[PDB]
Figure 1 (tube, each protein chain N blue to C red):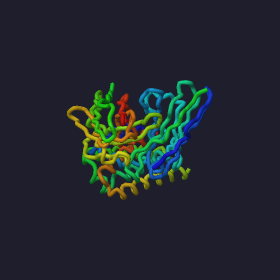
Figure 2 (spheres, each protein chain N blue to C red; figure 1 turned 90 degrees about the horizontal axis):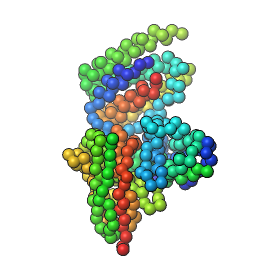
Figure 3 (cartoon, each protein chain N blue to C red; figure 1 turned 180 degrees about the horizontal axis):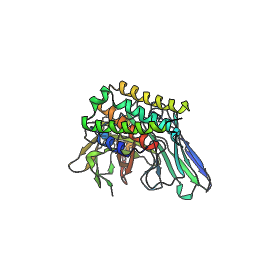
Figure 4 (cartoon, rainbow over the protein chains, first blue to last red; figure 1 turned 180 degrees about the vertical axis):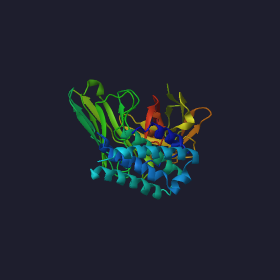
Length: 132
Length: 229
């Protein structure tokens, strides 16, 4: 719900300059419409997905140990907090899952390259900031 | 190669009007779209980026949209000051090139870039363009050159990474032009060789934000004319 902290850690995880990755960025079709009120089940799914995304072996390969840990533990509390309040539209939750496969597909295509990873890091930042 | 908009559109004040951008999916389908506005005489200014995002000062009657393989700029509460040319822009994953639409003439009822070196030359001649940059950390931004021929719309020419290790060119100028950079002196260059009469145009340098999906800032341009005279 409050992605400030996450956004900061993300901006700091950068290793390459996007200004060197001029032929890598991709529009992933973020389903922005599902966040304009925004159902919590789907906030949850967003954070949930981001968490699956960055706790892989490939992730741990790409990012700094310290930063990534702070980042992941934040997602970890966000999740727990979110999860309380989800006591109680599978259409939205689905669009979020799809979007995130478009992302891993991407990463696979690009052989998990540093430039590809920057694209993605930033892509998450965008989605985070657009989810509030 | 191409990315089409309606050559002209008009509306009355207070009206709402729409400007279409229709592309392939090697570009629009794949990539984030930006829009640029160009008042008569002025350099283009960024108007919409990442499909629907709006820069700082831009009124909110301006909105962007993307739908599979086409973009759309929408203006509401139309006003006489919106009279300008409007350009969509996107990267094309196939050609490894940026590209502008043919533009649309809308008829209504601290950072600095300074290009130099322009001038007048015989076909087959040579010129070197400089762009003096200031008000930001230059190394950290990719740059581009973009030209507008007499009476025509925007055409992307060349681009270069923050470091300098990556360069990109439009077919038009491939191998004749060479984009350079000296980050110790905050200058972008463009060596133009074997000049042609079609190279005639105002040359803008422009600063790429991040992954080069859009450029937020433009110089005022330097005029380059190629005539047998």
